[PDB]
Every structure is written in C-alpha cells, then in structure tokens.
Figure 1: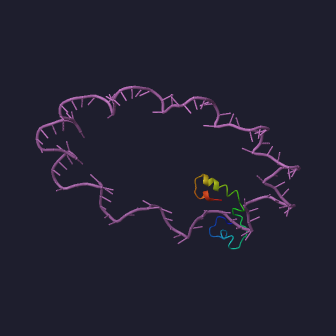
Figure 2: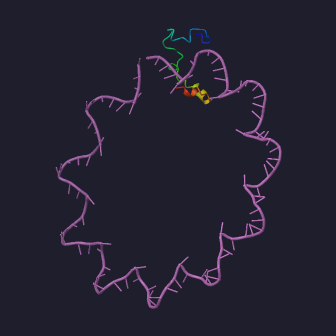
Amino acid sequence: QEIDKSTSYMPYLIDMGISAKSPYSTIKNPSFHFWGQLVAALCRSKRALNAR
RNA sequence: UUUUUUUUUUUUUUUUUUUUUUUUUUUUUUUUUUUUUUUUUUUUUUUUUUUUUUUUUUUUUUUUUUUUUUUUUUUUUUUUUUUUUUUUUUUUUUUUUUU
C-alpha cells in the first residue's frame, strides 16, 4: 500500500476517489484509537487529552 | 451516509534586546521631626469628706369574703351515604442514539 512514501497517492485516498471506505480511520479501527491515545495521555501529552 | 485534537499556509518558538548601562543614592554640609530662660501632680482660698438624714416608719400586703383565668344537660377519632383503595393502564412500545 506504499505506506512509507510521502510522494504517493495514499494520503489522498478519499478525495481522489480511489476508495470509499478507508481502512485507516477511527470508525474502521476503534479501540486502537483508544489504545495509544490513552497511553500518550498517561505519558503527559496534551494532544491526546482531547481524543474522543 | 461519512467521520472523530472546538490541530495545522509555509516558516518559526523570551508577550528579550539601538549602543551604553544598573542603589526609582548623592551640591557642599550635616543627622533627637531636643532646647529662650527656669521649671515639672493637666494638686491646693480656708474649711471640709455616705452625690445619708424633718419627725415617724419599713411586704411598691390586705373592705369582708374567697382561691381549676372548671362545669346548662348530654358527650368524647376536628371517622363514616353506599361502594371502593398504584394521584397505573387505548393498542403498541422503551438510549429525551443514528442519513
């Protein structure tokens, strides 16, 4: 899926019309958005205190 | 439906900086916000010392009675028509959730 390439089509997945249901979202991947964000909030980061 | 930092142009990151500076010190003197002199109870005329007293008195007691600010008699849930007894219910439903 060329994840690592900054000059590629992946970050414009939706607006290019390549895919309609992205496999990288919070709705597609809940409870991995709770993990990680909870860890960062418990590691005293102010960004993760606002994650839903 | 889709989403999920009320994040983001790129840069940047002391609500720091001319240069020089650093007692919101200083004329020189000075240093009781002391002092004429001499005094020192914001004492005293002499008397005097209950903001006591006419005498008499001494419950801010009393006419005599009296002594529940009780009582017609009867009574004694400031109960009761009967019936009743979720200030429940159409049916279906049951996140004041959702493209």
